[PDB]
Length: 366
Ligand SMILES: [Ca+2]
Ligand SMILES: [Ca+2]
Ligand SMILES: [Ca+2]
Ligand SMILES: [Ca+2]
Image (cartoon, rainbow, N blue to C red; front, side):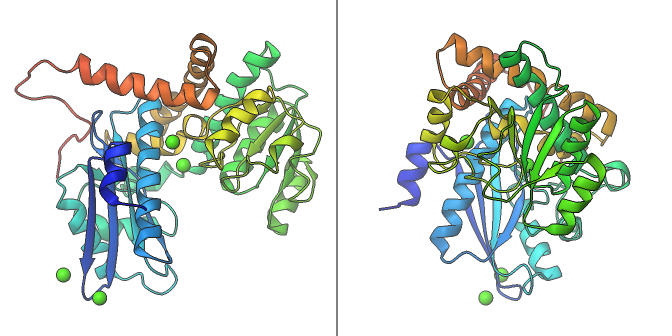
């Protein structure tokens, strides 16, 4: 059934750009959903898609995702995402990333790219050779801009906010948090949680990762399949997405979900289930926004203190989604979508009077 244009119509996508270069064998999709708030910011992601169609669907899905992520995050950015089709192991060249960066320069700052999955500051520095519409590449972001602890602080602050609602106190003192995954971002969330005096049950597909964790925080290890059934107050999915589904959600003994993974929900039903089951689902794209807020900050000359003080406010953003769920009698995830759509609409109206020059987040556009 799937028709590029019927999807763009139904979902209201602005632009989808297909890019090819001969010598680099570049096949790239830049997807731009909504730019009401400003330039579309979204990671470049490289992957071995089975078909053109697989890649388009992923590009579109992830682009609309950034529209909500960025809008809710209070950022003056739209929803975009780019995607290269190929083997990240074998097909990265200079020409690949230069050619792509040229096609990013072609859109004259409607798309701003950054590192995502299977792409690195090294790749972005090739893009940077052709365009200034790339972020996470400056000396300031290079020196003291190491992103993991900032995403983590976002998630930490958002969890605090959720706890205030259900428990009546934002203290995570003597709370048990089930933590799926102990990657960089998770490891740093564990640190804030241990320092507040919280009990940590964890899992990971990696053994060295697990032992580093139990060594440093004294966390009880548990089997990948057990983590959902475990007896804890808060579940924190920080590994993969679609971890909240038909199979896992009935197991949950927790009162809050508050993790770092993108697209925790496998389907929207799973949002409404967590609802019926009386579990407060603190939505992905609100809580883990810290990552995008960090690169967005570079656009204005990077300052980690300012980034952290802006991410500190993920608490206030979560608390607003809760308020909106109660007030509009909606499930958390649909309240977060509303909050983002309310803001887009509001600023589309509040800035609809003529100025010879409107100020946007591109300082010196290049
Ligand atoms: Ca060419
Ligand atoms: Ca070719
Ligand atoms: Ca979404
Ligand atoms: Ca992220």
